[PDB]
Amino acid sequence: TQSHYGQCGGIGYSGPTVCASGTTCQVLNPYYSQCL
Image 1: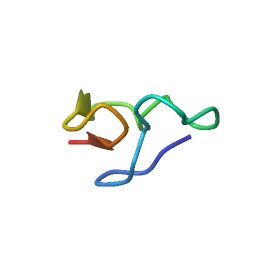
Image 2 (image 1 turned 120 degrees about the vertical axis):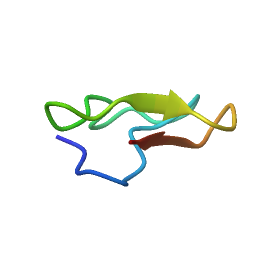
Image 3 (image 1 turned 90 degrees about the vertical axis):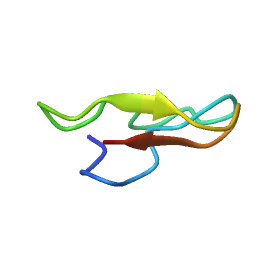
């Protein structure tokens, strides 16, 4: 799973798109999404 402040992933990311419980996957850029 994607750790806090890590890239959950935007378009193109096929792995841990799920963020750690409590953190929100925020798609900042279409390809860069971070777990805040």
